[PDB]
Amino acid sequence: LLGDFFRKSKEKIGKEFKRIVQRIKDFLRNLVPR
Amino acid sequence: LLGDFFRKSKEKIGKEFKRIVQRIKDFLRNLVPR
Ligand SMILES: CCCCCCCCCCCC[N+](C)(C)[O-]
Ligand SMILES: CCCCCCCCCCCC[N+](C)(C)[O-]
Ligand SMILES: CCCCCCCCCCCC[N+](C)(C)[O-]
Ligand SMILES: CCCCCCCCCCCC[N+](C)(C)[O-]
Ligand SMILES: CCCCCCCCCCCC[N+](C)(C)[O-]
Ligand SMILES: CCCCCCCCCCCC[N+](C)(C)[O-]
Image (tube, rainbow over all chains, first blue to last red; front, side, top):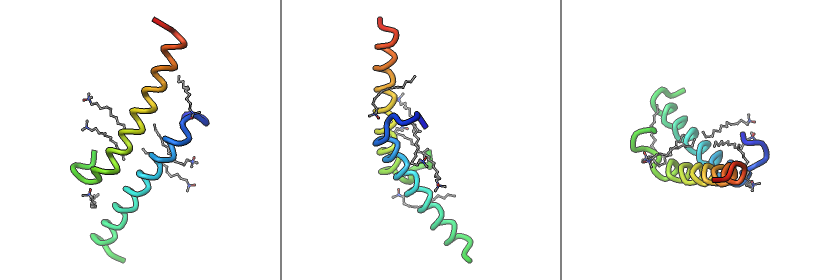
């Protein structure tokens, strides 16, 4: 986002967000399986 | 945001975001001091 500034912070944030999205995906796959 | 889910991730994200905002603040204070 902010150009090439805050590489480290932006990568940590992206990490956690991907973790969250993955767990929400797992949950929805258990809610409506297939 | 997502209720009480993802306490740990949400806290890490908040940490990094506050770091970023603080550094941007410092920068703007050097750009227009007072
Ligand atoms: C108007 C917003 C200005 C954003 C520029 C802030 C520059 C701060 C530089 C901190 C260093 C970040 N770095 C390169 C380690 O990622
Ligand atoms: C203050 C908002 C922070 C935004 C966080 C953006 C996370 C990007 C994670 C790495 C992936 C970015 N990339 C390389 C696809 O552009
Ligand atoms: C609000 C937290 C940060 C949001 C970051 C969103 C990044 C979405 C994933 C980037 C897509 C990269 N990909 C794999 C298509 O190349
Ligand atoms: C429609 C979105 C549904 C979101 C609910 C996902 C539940 C996943 C539970 C993972 C556990 C999270 N916890 C409690 C450790 O923070
Ligand atoms: C996927 C988006 C993540 C949103 C991150 C929200 C960070 C909140 C940081 C802790 C502060 C929240 N609080 C307690 C003021 O509500
Ligand atoms: C996109 C990354 C997450 C953004 C989190 C934004 C939180 C702003 C700070 C919350 C304000 C809490 N306070 C100190 C007024 O009580």
